[PDB]
Amino acid sequence: IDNGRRGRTVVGANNRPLKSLSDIIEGKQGRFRQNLLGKRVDYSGRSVIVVGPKLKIHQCGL
Amino acid sequence: QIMHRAEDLISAASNRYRITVQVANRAKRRRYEEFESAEDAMMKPVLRAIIEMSDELT
Amino acid sequence: MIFRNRVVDKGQLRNLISWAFTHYGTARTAVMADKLKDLGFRYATRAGVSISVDDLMVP
């Protein structure tokens, strides 16, 4: 249920505390807070940015 | 112009939401109905919808 | 219509804008805002305007 809660945190081949049921749904990265309020969609594109003179506002380069 | 219309549209109407949605569904119909009638590639059904709701309707 | 003789740069355009706003659409304003940034630039350029350790006067 919850590693590391009370007795001695289990540490397997991962050479570190394992990942109990609780904690995969907790923290900053509990399921909640990151796959769930914050998922990671497609239909996207990033880039650097640069002033787009000539191109007016309400427009973007692309 | 469409721009000023888009403005006037919601410069004197119901909840800016309330509008939209009905702009929306409208166009939805504007697309569903008249499905690919005039190509519309330029005047997106949404655009239509707007003008025919921001000038025609007004 | 209100002609305004004043040195415009920061704030002068700020409230301007608003003013516009209220009194006209957004849409317009925007397109104002634009045209004028556009000034902004080109004049700026035209002035040509550089700085330097010397430009750093000393009092």
Image: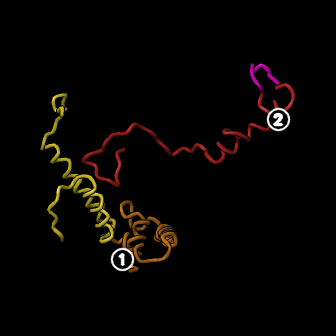
Residue C27 image offset from top left, x and y in percent = 32, 65
Which colour denotes chain A? Answer: red
Could you tell me which secondary element the residue under label 2 belongs to?
loop
x 58%, y 42%: residue: A40
Q: Reply yes or no: does residue A13 show up in magenta.
A: yes
Residue C12 image offset from top left, x and y in percent = 25, 58
Q: Specify the farthest residue to the bottom.
A: B58
Residue B1 is drawn in which quadrant? Answer: bottom left
Q: Reply yes or no: does residue B5 show up in magenta.
A: no
Quadrant showing the C terminus of chain B: bottom left
Q: Where is mark 2, residue-wise? A: A2
x 40%, y 69%: residue: B48
Comparing B44 with A53, the one in front is A53
Residue C3 image offset from top left, x and y in percent = 15, 67
Comparing B45 with C43, the one in front is C43
In the rendered view, tell whether residue C25 sits above or below residue C10.
below
Label the orange chain with its letter: B
Which colour denotes chain C? Answer: yellow
Residue C49 is drawn in which quadrant? Answer: top left
Q: Where is mark 1, residue-wise? A: B55
The magenta region covers: A10-17
Chain under callout 1: B
Q: What residue type is disc 1 on? A: Asp
Few, some or many C-alpha atoms within 10 Å of disc 1 (few <14, some 14-19, many ≥20)? some
Residue A51 image offset from top left, x and y in percent = 31, 42
In the rendered view, tell whether residue A29 sits above or below residue C42.
above
Few, some or many C-alpha atoms within 10 Å of disc 2 (few <14, some 14-19, many ≥20)? few
Dominant secondary structure of the magenta stretch? loop
Residue A52 is drawn in which quadrant? Answer: top left
